[PDB]
Amino acid sequence: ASIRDAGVADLPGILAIYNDAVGNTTAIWNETPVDLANRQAWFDARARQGYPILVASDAAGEVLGYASYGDWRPFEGFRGTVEHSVYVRDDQRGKGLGVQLLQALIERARAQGLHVMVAAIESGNAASIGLHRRLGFEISGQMPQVGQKFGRWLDLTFMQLNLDPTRSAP
């Protein structure tokens, strides 16, 4: 699959994947679906911040998956740190796309001179933690019952990857 920046024409495909995640998974901790205007606003905001929105596709040109990153925390002191999110279309799982999209984000982040990429993972997702681990992430936080979905408390696991370890200062 090819990976590249998203265009406005990829937004309805992205919308479908997203609304789908929020109502049937613990991958996204929102329960309310959004509309196209909402994603168009998100698309423009990422553009002003210089943050990428990547799309996995092929010859057919359909959105098989997407990924992006943005502010981890809203303060000037965290500008060297970003948090990512990756989503694969449901008929496309088990094909290694998630790893492809995450690796692409890491390359864009590194190229932009960012220092750390953070991952927030539902603690029960052992496979997701294992995949992030193989890519260089290390667990830096384990926070009990800070979230909730489908009527139950959720635990969050924080993982991080230092994009440039030899950089003694910003």
Image: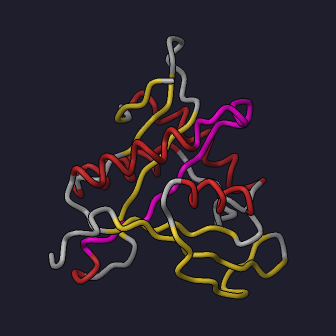
Give above or below for 124 relative to 58: below
Point out the residue furthest to the front here.
Answer: 166
Point out the residue furthest to the right here.
Answer: 151
Residue placed at 47% from the left, 36% from the top? 11
Point out the residue furthest to the left here.
Answer: 170
| Position of residue 54 measured from the top left corner of the image (x, y, whole percent) | 41, 40
Residue placed at 46% from the left, 51% from the top? 38
Residue placed at 68% from the left, 80% from the top? 147
* Left or right side of 162 for 55: right
**Residue 76 appears in which quarter of the rendering?**
bottom left
**Residue 4 appears in which quarter of the rendering?**
top left
| Position of residue 62 measured from the top left corner of the image (x, y, whole percent) | 54, 22
Give above or below for 7 relative to 80: above
| Position of residue 70 measured from the top left corner of the image (x, y, whole percent) | 37, 62
- Numbered disc total: 0
Does 91 lie within the magenta span? yes
**33 or 107: nearer the viewer:** 107
| Position of residue 64 measured from the top left corner of the image (x, y, whole percent) | 58, 30
**51 or 9: nearer the viewer:** 51
Residue placed at 46% from the left, 59% from the top? 84
Q: Which quadrant of the rendered structure holds the C terminus?
A: bottom left
Tell me the colour scheme of the image.
secondary structure
**6 or 85: nearer the viewer:** 85
> In the image, which residues are magenta?
79-98
